[PDB]
Length: 61
Length: 61
Image (cartoon, rainbow over all chains, first blue to last red; front, side, top):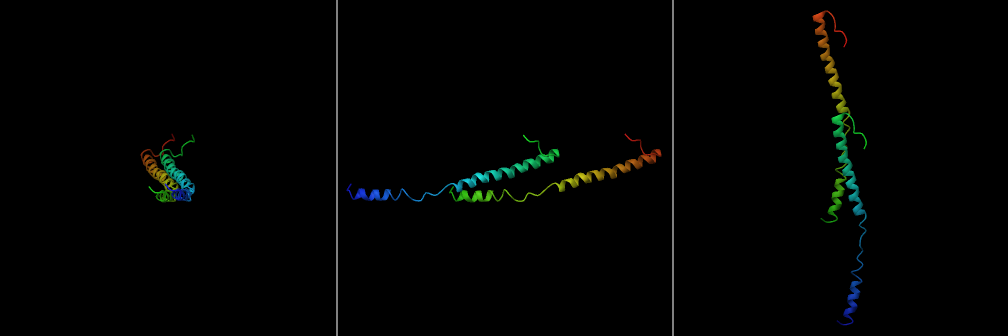
């Protein structure tokens, strides 16, 4: 509308364009880690189930 | 739901994935042993029954 109105908008667009976007890197690597430790604690039950069938842990591959 | 909610889950999955799984090796070898000593104490009764039939322990094989 008025030149002064178009001077507040550009003064607010500048504000709302920098709101300290956080580093969402550590908060995701923790999920990838806790998939692998879960997966290992599960894998152990398969190994120690299979031993109590065969008196041996499985052959590799 | 919220990023903080997905930060407690990964903080608990990490806990419940390490609960000091014990070594269930000695607690099974004892069973295998007590099968063999039972089996021997039984085998002795067959030998010393067979003697009191024949005046001799059996021939081998």
